[PDB]
Image (cartoon, rainbow, N blue to C red):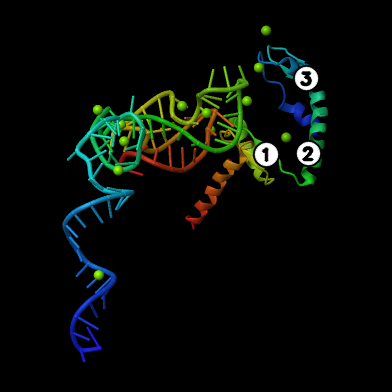
Amino acid sequence: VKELLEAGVHFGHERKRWNPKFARYIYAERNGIHIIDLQKTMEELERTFRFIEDLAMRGGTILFVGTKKQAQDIVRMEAERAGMPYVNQRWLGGMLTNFKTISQRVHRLEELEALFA
RNA sequence: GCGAGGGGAGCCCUAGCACAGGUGCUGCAUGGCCGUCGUCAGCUCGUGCCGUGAGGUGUUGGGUUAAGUCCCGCAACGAGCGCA
Ligand SMILES: [Mg+2]
Ligand SMILES: [Mg+2]
Ligand SMILES: [Mg+2]
Ligand SMILES: [Mg+2]
Ligand SMILES: [Mg+2]
Ligand SMILES: [Mg+2]
Ligand SMILES: [Mg+2]
Ligand SMILES: [Mg+2]
Ligand SMILES: [Mg+2]
Ligand SMILES: [Mg+2]
Ligand SMILES: [Mg+2]
Ligand SMILES: [Mg+2]
């Protein structure tokens, strides 16, 4: 059922902005718009969720992210409904890399709850 | 020591030694203090990111303000010397 749902209404959309690499992942390009390969997508989904199966059970944490409007809300509920980290708003430069200083802002957060109750 | 006479401290003259004192230089040897641009809106540090590097980014941009004042946006995130 996971396969036919995708085939339903969740594939192909972009046009005239394609990379040479995303081309081999393509199935066709009629009406002037690209059409992603559903078959290869499944196989990739398999390999991905395999990494998910390990990652989830390893106890590790996934950092979700999406600034696109169509994904801000979707990833929002789905990240909380899993307790996993995520950022829908404008991603900051250094969040992962310069993490030490980004955390200082998280520390400024607890200060708020202090003078909030 | 009853008296004579002797030495020391305080203080002086004369002779002699070490030394004092100098509004005599050098404000390009300096401390300190002061004028000045100008109360003008500025100048930087920490880490991250870009560049081979000098360095950039932040502090640029849009609105606003006496002001780097505040807001929104932002590969940047905070802080410090200033403004208040
Ligand atoms: Mg469905
Ligand atoms: Mg063409
Ligand atoms: Mg941002
Ligand atoms: Mg005598
Ligand atoms: Mg002399
Ligand atoms: Mg001088
Ligand atoms: Mg001087
Ligand atoms: Mg002179
Ligand atoms: Mg480098
Ligand atoms: Mg080179
Ligand atoms: Mg620099
Ligand atoms: Mg600069």
Image quadrant containing the N terminus of chain A? top right
Task: Please name the residue that numbered disc 1 is placed on.
Answer: A63
Say which label, 3 or 1, has the lower sequence index.
3
Q: On residue A52, which mark appears?
A: 2
Point 73% across, 13% down: residue = A29
Tell me the mark number nearer the camera, choosing from 3 and 1.
1
Where B9 falls versus B24 (above or below)?
below
Across and down, in percent, residue A38 comes to 79, 24
Say which label, 3 or 2, has the lower sequence index.
3
* C-alpha span from label 3 to label 2: 22 Å
Q: Count every numbered label the image shows and give the total.
A: 3
* C-alpha span from label 1 to label 2: 12 Å
Across and down, in percent, residue A65 comes to 64, 35
Name the side, left or right, on which A83 lies relative to B59.
right
Q: Chain of mark 2?
A: A
Task: Please name the residue that numbered disc 3 is placed on.
Answer: A25
Front residue (pair A53, B79)? B79
Crowding at mark 1 (Cα within 10 Å: few <14, some 14-19, many 20+): few
Across and down, in percent, residue B80 comes to 43, 43
Crowding at mark 2 (Cα within 10 Å: few <14, some 14-19, many 20+): some
Point 54% across, 52% down: residue = A110
Point 52% across, 54% down: residue = A113
Where A102 falls versus A113 (above or below)?
above
Asked which quadrant contains residue A36, the reply is: top right
Say which label, 1 or 2, has the lower sequence index.
2
Front residue (pair A2, A81)? A81
Front residue (pair A12, A8)? A12
Q: Chain of mark 1?
A: A
Q: Secondary structure at mark 2?
A: helix
